[PDB]
Image (cartoon, rainbow, N blue to C red):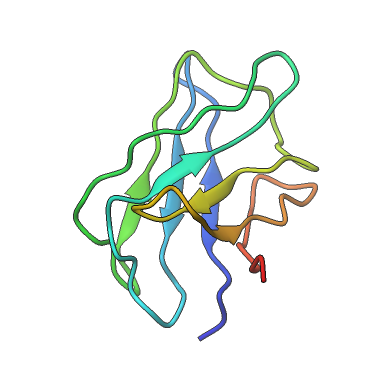
Length: 103
C-alpha cells in the first residue's frame, strides 16, 4: 500500500537518530543500506540489519556524529542487499520522509 516510507529525524542526544518503518506493501528483504547527504559532512552508507523489518516493523540508522536538520533537498535514499537504490526519499521540508521510487 503505497511505497511511501515513513521516517523520523531525531537529530539529538549529541548525535543522530533515524527511524524508518516499512509501510510499503512488500516487506524489506534485509541487509539493506542507507545513504544520506549533507553540507557539513559528506554522504555515507550505514550497514543495516540483515533481518527484515515488516509492514509495521521499524528500523534504526544511528549515525555519528550527527547532521543538521531537516534534511530537505537531501538524498537519504535506500539501497538493497546489493547496494542498489531500491527507493528514494523525497526529503521534503520536514523531518518526515516518504520514499517514492526511482524508476
